[PDB]
Length: 212
Ligand SMILES: *[C@@H](C(=O)NCCc1ccccn1)C(=O)C(=O)N[C@@H](Cc1ccccc1)C(=O)N(C)C
Image (cartoon, rainbow, N blue to C red):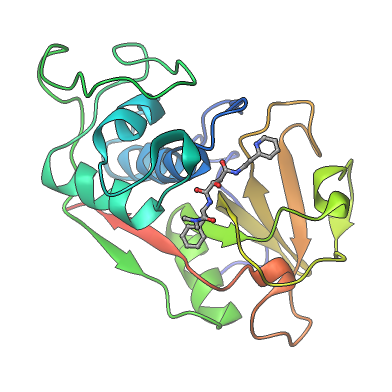
């Protein structure tokens, strides 16, 4: 697989969003992967609804947190609407999937990347954007402004983001904290250190949707 991968260059990544004060990272992470796979499969880059997942995935806790796997399972079973049809409000409301008409896209399943394995994650990233988790609680992560992030951070994963690329010494991540955070909304996290958990526990729980 290539030495450098960047899904933004291939037109598979939509603009950076801001989740606000709502703990909806899981929904954002899941949506990036859906937007990516639909582009790779159909050739069309569309934006999908984080709000729908927030309101409809009852296995998750709305603005209190949730699971990317669960959100991806919901899109596989039912489907998802376009972001303009069901826009982000930043607050959990009732599931409005029904009133908004037929779904825009549907996936066929979800697979998990072999955890604690850098190679497995890089292979998945080379194929499509992947939902990954990491420890974001530390002030070093929160105040990241640029460069290759090496930490400091432990492996107490608490934030769901998405891997959209990589390079020789980094994994490119799309965060959901607005364009003013990090590298225009992105973070390049150090890879190849020999830490099985990954920098900030990056290799703990990674999922991607299956289409076709
Ligand atoms: C993610 C959330 O949105 N966190 C960001 C909060 C923040 C900080 C600064 C500025 C703006 N927003 C959310 O908590 C969440 O859903 N966390 C999950 C991640 C996870 C971890 C392991 C497996 C699956 C999902 C979480 O910690 N739990 C579900 C426990």
